[PDB]
Length: 109
Image: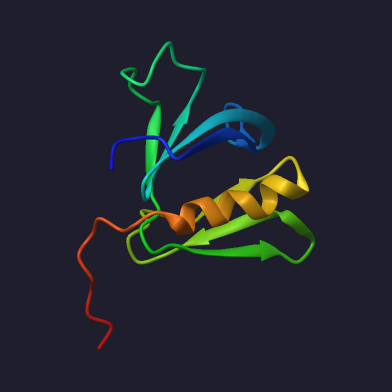
C-alpha cells in the first residue's frame, strides 16, 4: 500500500542490551510495520526499521493479554509488541488483519 492505516505507541524491550521497557512510535502501512526512534516530520521520513507482518499470527501472552507474540513464515524473527491500553490490545491486531497481503502465497505441502 504505502499509505498509513493505523499508528500509535507500544512498549518493547530496549536499552543497550534490549532488556529495558521502553516506548517507541509504531506506524502501520498495509501488511508492513514501521517503527521509529522518534516521531517523523512527515510520511516522507524514513523509519528506523520495518517488520513484515504479512499473514502473521498474533497470540496473547497468558500472563499479559497486552503483550502480543508475533510469528509467521514471512517474519524475519519472533517479535513482542506490548500495548498500553485494553482498546489498543484488540485494535492493534485487528488493524493489522484488515490490511491485504502483498507477498505471494507459499506452499505448505
